[PDB]
Length: 120
Length: 119
Image (tube, rainbow over all chains, first blue to last red; front, side, top):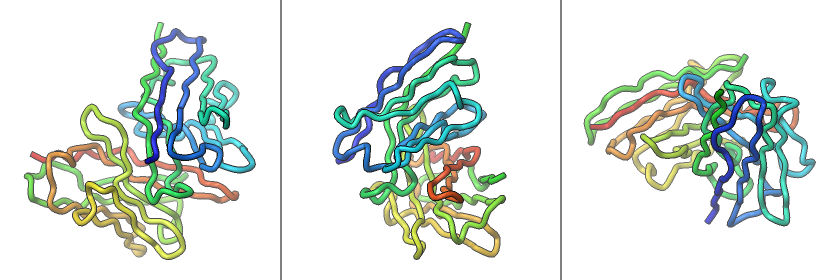
């Protein structure tokens, strides 16, 4: 069955960086509209970035544009989120995530959640 | 600006029932795809149900099939989640959701989250 396994993340200082990885299995990441959703207590949920299937064109939230870069390595079946110039407000649990309506599976799916933290 | 405002959360004894509501604004819900996500204490996100496509087809997580019902009231512009036969596993913060594509591809939205506790 379909699975998303996140790695990377941790604790860094402001201005630093981290690369999240999301290794998919049971399907091909290039065929799906994939993305990252972050969750902080008090700010609910938010689509930080996505890459939508064929084109490979990309969305970004206004707050992260210029700093964050979503990408894919089809040979490794892995989605990435290069997070540069990190700020204190980026502090959240980041989730690899399919769209509301995936290409094949009837319901959307999620990775396990990866805590990223930015503090001095 | 699109907004999703959830209400109807609270404490409920096992076996009982509870209806989450989600008042949508900035758009109309009859057309767009919507759903409900949840996060049980300490655990990760999980789609609970969604309603999408031309015909308003509904889909359910394996663990909530037969108990939960997603629906739309186009007149009130509100998405619902009727939760019957509640158990301890349903203890979670529930998030309304939608997906709008004004230019070819989905942007995603979420509500604030509402706590439902079963005990």
